[PDB]
Image (tube, rainbow, N blue to C red):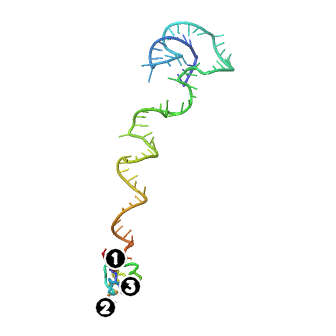
Amino acid sequence: MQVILLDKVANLGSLGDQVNVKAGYARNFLVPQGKAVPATKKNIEFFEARRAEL
RNA sequence: GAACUCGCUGUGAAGAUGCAGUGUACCCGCGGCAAGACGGAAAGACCCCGUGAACCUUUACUAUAGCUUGACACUGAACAU
């Protein structure tokens, strides 16, 4: 779903963009194995500050 | 059910110990034999009814467990023909 990436994962990733992917690829691979974070409307404002400040 | 509980012919819910006619018979036991009293025993089991019941059977009706087909969800990413 609306998950935001953090890693060099293959061609849907650009070090973090909101994509439209299925929920099966969301959980257990992106929801924690690393490499991403769920977007439960709290991380879309927290990691947005990580984009601007860094 | 009660009886002081005879046989005939005929009558009769159509096979009479009780009716009618008639015949016969002292009163009362006991030992016997089963002919009858449509004997006793079982609201006939056979048969037919009841818009009875019960099971069982099937290409009766309508359901359903299970089996089976497909879709969605659990369930993904890359691709290619």
Q: Are marks 1 and 2 on the same chain?
A: yes
Secondary structure under the numbered disc 2 in the rendered image: helix
Q: Are marks 2 and 3 on the same chain?
A: yes
- Give the letter of the chain under mark 2: A
| Circle 3/circle 1 CB separation < 8 Å | no
CA separation, marks 3 and 1? 16 Å
- Residue in the image at 31% along x and 84% along y: A17
Q: Quadrant of the N terminus of chain A?
A: bottom left
Can you give x and y, in whole percent of width and height, for residue A5 in the image? 35, 84
Check disc 2 and give the amino acid type: Ala
CA separation, marks 1 and 2? 28 Å
Depth check, front residue: A12 or B65: A12
Depth check, front residue: B34 or B21: B34
CA separation, marks 2 and 3? 20 Å
- Residue in the image at 40% along x and 84% along y: A34
Q: Nearer the viewer, mark 1 or mark 2?
A: 1
Which dot marks residue A12? Answer: none
Residue under numbered circle 3: A35
Residue under numbered circle 1: A22
Secondary structure under the numbered disc 1 in the rendered image: loop
Residue under numbered circle 2: A52
Categorize mark 1 by other alpha carbons within 10 Å: few (<14), some (14-19), many (20+). few
Check disc 1 and give the amino acid type: Lys
